[PDB]
Length: 219
Length: 218
Figure 1 (spheres, rainbow over the protein chains, first blue to last red):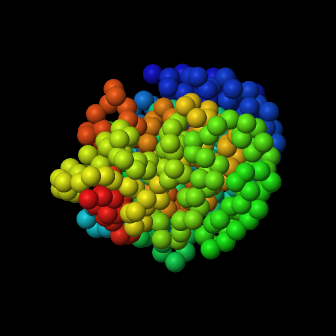
Figure 2: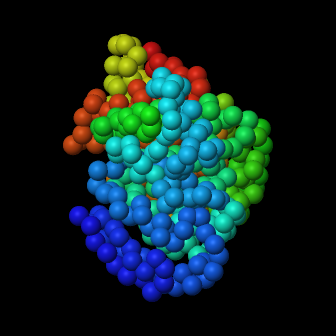
């Protein structure tokens, strides 16, 4: 179910799943407006990995786990992913799921291999080593894409109370938005955060299947 | 424990200390719209508009919210029913009855429950007309709800259609659930699990549960 459109600058070709179709024209238009600017910065991730998450189906997703932007370094295009399992954020998320599920022995963790879950970066790049530095470039695109995502998922789970302090939640909507502590914050706080369990309670209340968070583990 | 003056009726607003950081803008916003708002007969009466501001907020962990007051005989206390005839509070009491096991009762009040603040998003309607003062309360409503959600752990909105266009900067801290309106005649509120799930959500947020049985009047 894959398609392809072209943008005037790198990565030139953008692959996407059918479910993203209603957005892709405005996306191409918007990205052509800012690409020349942001590409003059070296970025995390690299341009070829900006949009790889658009390959994912959305209709089978019921939970979005969203961070504000990619890792300052070594981003892969897949939000929170750390191939060698070294980034603090994914390690803490893993520790939380470890205590939750009883899985003690694991090599890594990836939110992208969990049924029903799509991990998301609100901004799709940052200047290398500088968090939120590409906000002005992704702004319009960021609203466009997230709004489309929340047309499919039942729960939007944002990580970072400061980062998402001004997010406007739509009540009725059929989408519940919760904002938790950033996993790489301070004074634990994220560790005692039970947002993953809360999500499943919300899902089951909405008569949806719950998330099997243990699926994220890599052995 | 406090008081401020406004230019139109009810001319004065009494409030608890916890509402202090909001009262500056509230007076300003109310003076802007009160003139048009007051040309209609309202439910509730102007002197009952803000009586829920007398409630403490620091000791509240659950907000139960309707879109606006009942079009007749509103008391300023959301969902309150003196003679216990409004279908809303009766369906609610019925649900709480099943949850708590309390069988015999002659009434129910959400406003006498520790940790719970009943709320109406819009603070008035024209007498006999539902959702008619949305355009006057809009700014005020966002301000007051945002403040509440700085304190409560769970926000329970009743009426999916009613709240379908409402957006809010929740922040927190706050888990939101939106359920069917209790007075809906196409729905069976007995099948609603919202009240039961609230205490689960509170436990997951490491808070004490709500004792819903405190609502019963005997």
